[PDB]
Length: 350
Ligand SMILES: [Ca+2]
Image 1 (tube, rainbow, N blue to C red):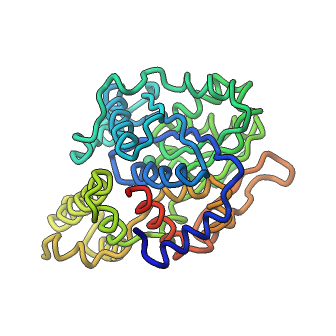
Image 2 (cartoon, rainbow, N blue to C red):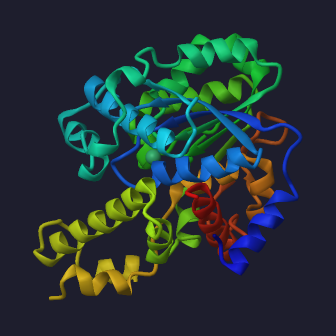
């Protein structure tokens, strides 16, 4: 069940269903934060409503065994969302410094019990995506909400196909100051594998495939409150309880760390200014602002939802391969984006 205003926004989106669902290839790094799994959850409702069909997911971030743990978790979540036919595969190796090893090996305890068995996920990265680009009668969309090792691998291995079978590439990323458009080395997903990010941004443009880049500023504007997570956990859906528990515990850990001055450069003032001697139970209720970067990227990737919420700004040189930017100014309906994200996640968890 939805609230009156949630039910209305979902009715409104439903007027804009496409004739055919858009087949979708997703590149993702779940269980180091809530974002990717919120995206899988809203994708379930978008699939149920005929906007997309999530055919293949390739998982990155970490060494080979870590990528398999993430892929097992993704497949576990798709199973619990009754998306039984999503094909999940581990992505390929990529270069990691010692500093990256620590961050890229983050795997939140709440996801451990959600993992499908190891043999439920595939080890051959983008092979199935290649075969599917070959045999699709209609163009597919590519959505990147993680590092780009595999997305770039796909454009490289199937460069012949992608030119005629991929409609757009939408990325949670960032555009470097200097230009062809190239990736910002500071943006998290680009920094996961910066050479692959450069190869992808560059090759998409050489191949004439439209790029749409959603940046962290777009999410700030449409940040959701804790009620978003409490709403989806309310009825005991395991994916809803996972999301609320991961967000609440991540935030608890950040609060406690700052309280003890253990996170250099951050302080109580930064925490109140970002999210708003206390225990975390007295802070959780004051929080009002939680970012959903990856779900917004997915909303930006589908024309039906994009036209509802966004007015992307073109960044390419007049006449060149299109590159659009979605930042704070381009999120034109943020309260509607908030309400639509809540509507989709609650409907998905029925
Ligand atoms: Ca992500």
